[PDB]
Image (cartoon, rainbow, N blue to C red; front, side):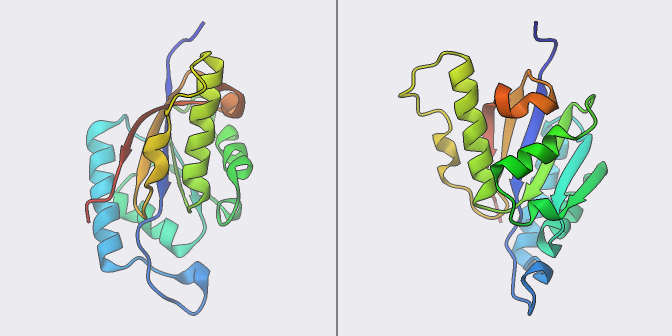
Length: 172
């Protein structure tokens, strides 16, 4: 039945400064360091990212740039303030044979998305409904990412859910 797991990385952009338009706010120097560290970790520890879905905001674009990940990128205004359902609709639309997908977006939606996927996966696995699975997402500062795994096709992610593997917190 399953035939391999797909890897989903849900990232909140790194720390950003001030600008006269919110969408133009740049990373701070500490946010650049945090995004750089996150990229180094991702490229050293996970399969190469195949597809990135990224908010059009400067800070999300810049976070991606700082990671050093070269992949096909889908920039989406839907990720600039979209909710869980919008983020999942965009993940569902990626090339189906992608093995590893990175999402670079904003809180609160990014951690909420992870949490919903975890709870759906619990349900599908007939887990104990008092399970604390997903509680690691309770801290999700700028630059954090969660790594999840699913056996479902990308299109089916909302129904299939995903299991949380790790949450990597910013180190700068």
